[PDB]
Amino acid sequence: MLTEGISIQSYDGHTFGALVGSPAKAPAPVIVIAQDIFGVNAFMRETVSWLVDQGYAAVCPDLYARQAPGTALDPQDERQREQAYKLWQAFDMEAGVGDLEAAIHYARHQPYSNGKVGLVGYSLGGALAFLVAAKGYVDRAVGYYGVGLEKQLNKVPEVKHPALFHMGGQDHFVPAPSRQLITEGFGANPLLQVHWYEEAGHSFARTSSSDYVASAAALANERTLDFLAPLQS
Image (cartoon, rainbow, N blue to C red; front, side, top):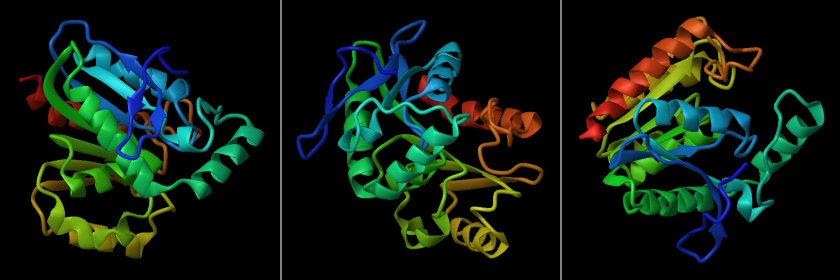
């Protein structure tokens, strides 16, 4: 689901919609949420809700609009999971970072904006959160269980604003040698923070996931809110 009428233009001209939640009280910092592989669906609506209840405005852009605008898939349906994997396999990561840059720029200047912008992403969006932190586009970035971060470690020195990553110790997208690489590489830059949740696997913060772990989702989420709070000005 997206908010009717909202349109954001990316550097190359492509336009895309977004699900927007204005804030209870304005002006407020705005958090751009980078979707998982299921598009802007029920979990994104819930994330927008969560952030608005904590005092932020939130913008979740339709990153699949270059392939299939308005895609919103149910992760409980087998056929739509297969569709999510097919879209993820074809996803242009650099164009997604470009679309997030445009959504971040939009987030800076809405009527309810206080000018500060954060980004929170999950899975596919957690890997995009790291690439966005390397570009420097946001004030703070947060990535939950981004996939393939051990292949992007040469960008660690480019991160110049804070970025927080929550990783599951039982997420098999990140086996032990990958964990160690990430832990050692991120460890060289104090602007990066990574926490490992030993009893949790991938998607552990989505309440509707079979891999949901309440204690870890809760510890992660509070660390995310404490990390984003300085943007409240």
